[PDB]
Length: 56
Image (cartoon, rainbow, N blue to C red):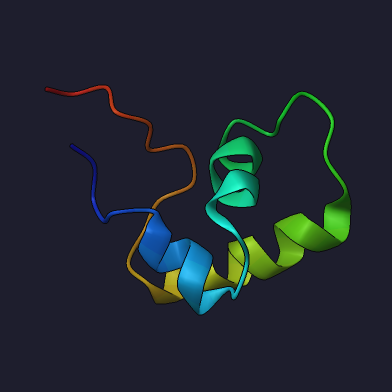
């Protein structure tokens, strides 16, 4: 599926899931501040930047 259910990142970063999956692929253009919060959360939750459902 992926290293961790991204709702976990979303929730720890305190932000609606809509942001996180968008952030992940950089939503072509997204606001920096959003990224900074997710970015912090990411490392902390043993997660790795661009882990979309592509392995299985």
